[PDB]
Length: 259
Length: 259
Ligand SMILES: CCCCCCCC/C=C/CCCCCCCC(=O)OC[C@H](O)CO
Ligand SMILES: [Cl-]
Image (cartoon, rainbow over all chains, first blue to last red; front, side, top):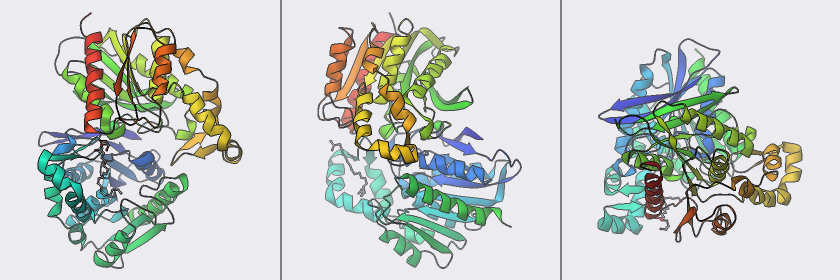
């Protein structure tokens, strides 16, 4: 079953979707999904919706919200910063924990690109109550990625405008200042539960090498990678998408359902 | 006021968003918005969401649903045809008509790309009860767009797969067969109320010349085109989407609010 849900906090309203298994009523495992930069809760070629329905089938529920300033949620994109999305995330996890259908023992996190960076930080911040973590092409190098564009053109354009057009989105000065001061690798360092990284070798938004760094610097043996040969950033093909979803569902099955 | 809404018919659930102007009294004008091919109700850089909020501020309400097979709604893309989206649209119109807050005499349609083809056909079908029509990069040439693509490669792939992968979506043989049978130009002919066409000269998905054909063939002097120079398909810049939205709202303001 699928229903729209809301969260209202600090005069901000977040809008999202909630899934629960049909044939398994009771208290269930839940996966929270965080979308990427300029993405939304449906995500690229509806891959998050597909993921929710795949989890539903094996008895795991999920929620996925639009961050403030994105998609269906309140706010202008120019009001959003990484930190503001981090705050959204905490409010989202709280929402999940308070559902009478939520098994508070078996809660997992999933994030794509910048949403993957959110997930890593949230997972660690709550390491004692997040049972598993899946990272899709995690943009742990986001601050660096953004800082480079700043020196290339953003800095110059922002100096003059206070923002930059990144394609029908007003990216504000406050975003670049906020994220320049953050290090995602470090804020994710220290999560001990199971971790799945899924990444396409041919990713051109978040280079595949970023996942090497994460395995090395951030997690130990608890982290495993699923490499998808030739795949682009959001796994933009039926078989790339199928692989990413099945591996992630299998992983969440083993980690959230058993014992 | 923004709230999630739901339609069900023939075992299909459509999920959408509804906007109403805050505490204006009694029934209000409504704009129904149809998203494009592989798009969803949020649409490119949230332009539909932005269009909805801009309409709300001038006292015009709106609804935006995901077509069956897309976004948050039920179904896989493989089940969708142009005709099934037409049927969705008829159910969405009915839904809007039967809301207590709807002024039945002031309903307008807006459609992007293939959603524009939908709106054009629906506008004609209900020409006596659709007050105004707005078309964004209307893909009235969708049949030949696909048929070109079909004869090139689809046949062999279709036979053994039943679909082709258009990038994380199953485009079915049924879609191709169904669309070949339609003439959106002829099906849209005869809508005699006001029409606004907004189209970018650098549209790489629906070539600007299609709008020429539509003005020449489909409508009379009741149709007007706003040309956005250099813009791509979904007006992917701050200035372009602003112009598309504002011209569209002004048009709807003029057509829906007084006469
Ligand atoms: C390789 C992927 C990027 C990796 C690095 C981080 C990028 C973060 C944001 C990038 C948006 C880049 C494209 C921005 C395009 C803006 C176009 C625009 O402003 O208007 C449209 C057109 O240029 C007429 O004006
Ligand atoms: Cl929604």
